[PDB]
View: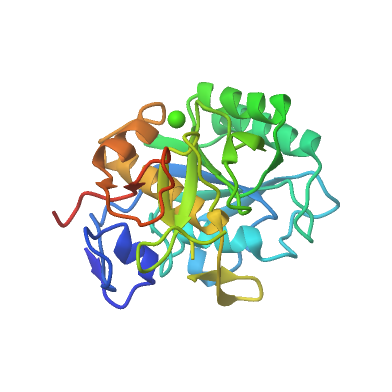
Amino acid sequence: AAQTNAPWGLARISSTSPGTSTYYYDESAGQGSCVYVIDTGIEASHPEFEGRAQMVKTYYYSSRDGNGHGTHCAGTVGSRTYGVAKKTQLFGVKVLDDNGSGQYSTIIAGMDFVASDKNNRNCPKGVVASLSLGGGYSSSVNSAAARLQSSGVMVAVAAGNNNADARNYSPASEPSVCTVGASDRYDRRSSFSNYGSVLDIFGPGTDILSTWIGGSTRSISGTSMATPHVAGLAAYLMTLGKTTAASACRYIADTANKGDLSNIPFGTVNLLAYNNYQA
Ligand SMILES: [Ca+2]
């Protein structure tokens, strides 16, 4: 399948080179997988989700995304137009309030909640979680990420937005999950991407067009926008039979475009998420 004049990040993760705008992909498009977006929620009523998105948990007084962040992430995972895995089932877990912020203990609560709930959902092809959030190192936050991963969920986490080595940030530093940095449409590391040997992979994160609340769209930027490109991609790869929730971060690294980002500080991977469809 091909989708012309695509947001640029969807073309990138289907390209070897930058500078094009079609998204080439297999039509199975993540059918039969599932992705949890653990964030401010998901405006599931956005027609771009076409009935495939459900809130299923909140730790606040409403499950609605009243911020838009969670809705934008989720759109990149699996909206019809702006998504990677255009036919995956989405699930929302509102651990962030509406300004964006969340205490660690609630973020922990929502992470253990996915390891349990996946057992209440129909995900024959695999299950993913997408965490576009974080804050300073915590053993506990990190441990809640290893559990979620260990429970057979592919966990994708934002490396962080300070340009700082991410080993000081959680859940990014947690080694057993898949820590994602951001790039730009000219293959530069985005100016705000954390970096450091705990990263596994980069995806698109600078000027990422996706859904927003009010039925709407916007382009915003972050390792947060990069993260749901890897999550959606892993859903897409499960479904295709290429990899498994426990093997997907290694498979994506193995199949990445290798060398191609400029400003990888020394010691940081220079691997860019690629779908290995058109070549
Ligand atoms: Ca890893």
